[PDB]
Length: 61
Length: 61
Image (cartoon, rainbow over all chains, first blue to last red; front, side):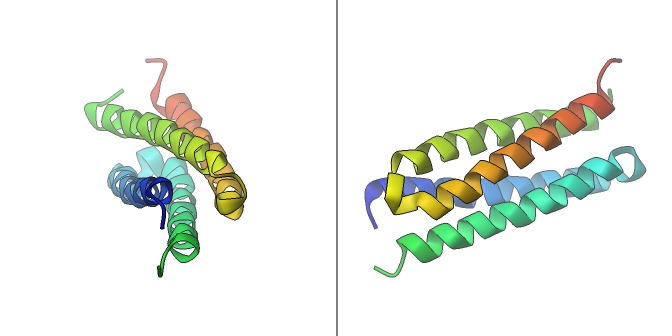
């Protein structure tokens, strides 16, 4: 892939990892952050979908 | 807010900022990352919704 695509792929990997870390933190606050943990769950799945879409488009090459 | 809520709010702010940076990068690659830029657009809006939900729940106090 190009260098510019590699930066974007690396950034998508990082965001997926940070949204998982934040989901864990919101889940640890239990009832105090319940709605927020539910939104973040969907955010993490959305981050994972973006990362896999970038890997598929820019990789194997 | 508590210290634990402040960590989660700060993390949600950071993720919102990183998803905007990644959206700009994917938009700069134009047709080469078009589907990915469309997914990331929705990701950034989702990140913004999470941050505003955390600010509303944990703030003004």
